[PDB]
Length: 198
Length: 198
Figure (cartoon, rainbow over the protein chains, first blue to last red):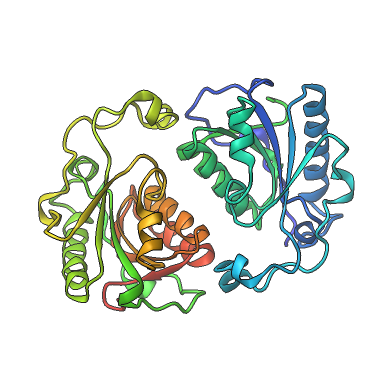
C-alpha cells in the first residue's frame, strides 16, 4: 500500500544456482496482475509504474521468443466452499476489477488460467501443459511476492520446474517483504534474476 | 547449526484465525525428525533438548487422544532424477542416519511416509489418507521451520487442511528463521500454537 522503490539488481541477493533461461524450455507466468490487486498501491506511485514497464517489456520479449505467456487471475464472487480457508484470512474474495490491468491486457495468443490458491499450480492445467510442451523453466512476475509469487515458485521447484523470480518485475506489500522473498527464493527454491540479465 | 533457545510462547505472533484442534479431525505430523537432520545441531545444546522433550510429550498426548502419528523421513541414496532440483541446493542428499532420533522412535500404531520434497504432501499418501479418514487438521512439529514445516503448512492450507504449527515444538537454522516462520504462518496460512495451549 505504501510507496516504495523496486530494489536495484546490485542489491539482489546472490544466487546459489547457475541456471540460465532458454526459450524452448521457458514459460512466462504473469501472476495476478489484476486491477483489484494493483488498486492497493497508488498506480501513479512506485513500485507500480516501473513494475508495469518491465513486465510489458518482458512479455514483449516473450512473444518474440515464442515463450508462452500465461496470465493467472482470481475469479469474482467465489463459491465459499471453493475458496475454503482463504476466507478465514482474506474475507469473501474479490467482486470487481477482475480483469488484467490495462497496459498488460493479453493479446490473442496468450493463455489465461483461473487461479484458486496462492500457488498457480493448484487446480490449473499449468503443470500438465508444461509437461506436454517439454517446458521446465518458469519465469515469474507480478504480485504479491511473498504470497502468490513465493508459493507458485515453491510448487514449481517441487514439481521439478526451475523457477526464475524476476526481482525487478515483482512487487509486494513492502520493500521488506519484497527483499525477504528474494532472499528466500535465492536460498531455498530458485533463481532471482533481472530484466537486464534476462 | 548454531545453538539457540526456543522462543517463549509469550513472544509468539498472534493468530489471525480462531481454529481449535479437535481430536476426531486431527493428525500429528512429526516432520523430518531424522538423525541426519538433527546432527546439523549440537544435540546437547539448545534448541534440541527442548524440541525433543516437547515432541515426546505432545506425541504421547496424541496417542492418548487417538490422533494418528505420521512421521516423515527422507530416504538414503536418492536417484538423482527423483531428487531433481534439490541437489542443486543441497547436494546429493543423505546416505545414513535415516532413522528417527532415538527419543522419538515410532511405536506400534504409527505410520512412516517417505519424504521427497519440502512439502510432506508431495508424492505421499498423506492427502489421500486424510480424505478417507475425514481428517482436515494437521498438527506440525519437527525441523526445519522455514523450509519443510512452512512448505508443508502452505500445501496443507491450499489442500483445505488446517495446519497447526506448534511454535515451541519446531526448530530452524536460526532463531531469526524460527520467528519469521511463525510470523508468516500466522499472517498467511494457519495457526501458530504452543504445547500448553494445545
